[PDB]
Amino acid sequence: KSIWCSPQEIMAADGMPGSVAGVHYRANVQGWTKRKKEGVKGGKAVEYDVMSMPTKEREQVIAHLGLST
DNA sequence: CCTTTTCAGTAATCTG
DNA sequence: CAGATTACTGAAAAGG
Image 1 (cartoon, chains in turn green, red, purple):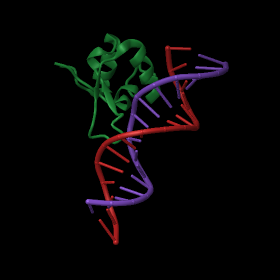
Image 2 (cartoon, rainbow, N blue to C red):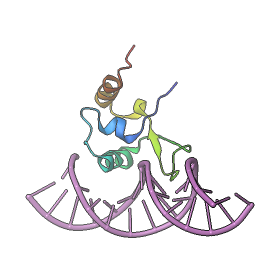
Image 3 (cartoon, protein in one colour):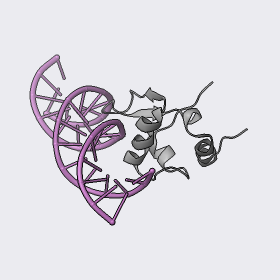
Image 4 (spheres, rainbow, N blue to C red):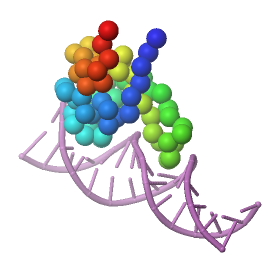
């Protein structure tokens, strides 16, 4: 299985830069997987695999998301 | 390592 | 249908 989120959801997670572009930073540098969205205008909108973010970061996102078990 | 600004394309949306 | 606009991000650069 896997999960995906929009930069605004991740950038809002602790441990994350805190800026839409900041996310793209680690994204290309770390090589985050990305699901290209479509229903969103511009079509440039793409989510990133939270299951691919640093283990520590995942907890920030999973906790920011409130998923966990 | 992070922050912020500008640039550009298309995508969907709205009307007569 | 036709024309037109707005709206949405992504990308890069520079500096502390």
